[PDB]
Image: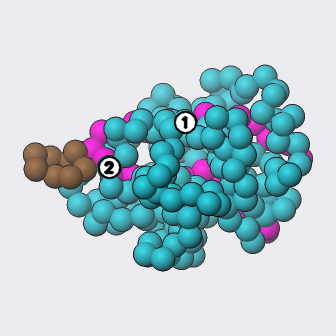
Chain colours: A brown, B cyan
Amino acid sequence: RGDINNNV
Amino acid sequence: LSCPEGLEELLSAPPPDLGAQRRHGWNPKDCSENIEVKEGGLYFERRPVAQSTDGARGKRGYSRGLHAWEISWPLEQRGTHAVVGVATALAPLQTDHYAALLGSNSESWGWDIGRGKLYHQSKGPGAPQYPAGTQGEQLEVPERLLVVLDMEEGTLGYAIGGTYLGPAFRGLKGRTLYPAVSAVWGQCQVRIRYLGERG
């Protein structure tokens, strides 16, 4: 959640 | 007129079957700790890991002749840094920030399929565009692209929709080079399909 690259 | 010798022959031969694809596919024993190789090498899945770039190599390194493989990398799974190319056996496969890892060092050569830029020993700003006469903002690499490694001339280039786009990198003679990518996208699925060899 919140990350530009779909990581979280 | 820039194609490697025997490219049309290779691309028109019956495609290597799943067995061949797994033999020349991603190596579970040669990838980032944050990548899981699936289907015995046919594709990988990058785990969701924040602030990481992650690479994988194929199982087989090429030193002679012509080899080609198709990479399938969904457009929506590329994120900020999606790089496609080759690496030596010694290239690093992980770094703790988002970056064009592949092509950042002596041991790797990459095409940034979002920006259009070529990286070898390059941090990224100033890198040249490929193919000739194009730029990121006005091109879109589709889901599937071919990677074409000519180890007799010592070149790496790419083909899109069956059309070779020219040599991207030169000076590769005498090296042993593996298929490679680097990725930043959580849960991206990158497939590799070996297309054969001649040589």
**Is B145 rendered above or below residue B181?**
above
From the viewer's side, name the closer residue of B155 and B159: B159
Image coordinates for residue B34, horizontal then vertical, percent: 32, 50
Q: Secondary structure at mark 2?
A: loop
Label 1 environment density (alpha carbons within 10 Å; few <14, some 14–19, many ≥20) = some
Q: Going by the picture, which residue comes out furthest to the left?
A: A1
- Tag 2, which chain? B
Image coordinates for residue B147, horizontal then vertical, percent: 65, 47
Q: Secondary structure at mark 1?
A: strand
**B186 relative to B150 in the view: left or right:** left
Residue ID at (68%, 65%): B169
Q: Mark 2 — residue?
A: B79
Q: Mark 1 — residue?
A: B144
Residue ID at (49%, 36%): B143
**B190 relative to B9 in the view: left or right:** left
**Is B44 rendered above or below residue B61?**
above
Label 2 environment density (alpha carbons within 10 Å; few <14, some 14–19, many ≥20) = some
Let me know if residue B125 appears in the view.
yes
Q: What segment carries the magenta color? A: B172-199
Report whether mark 1 lies on the same chain as mark 2: yes
Q: Amino acid at mark 1?
A: Arg
Residue ID at (51%, 72%): B127
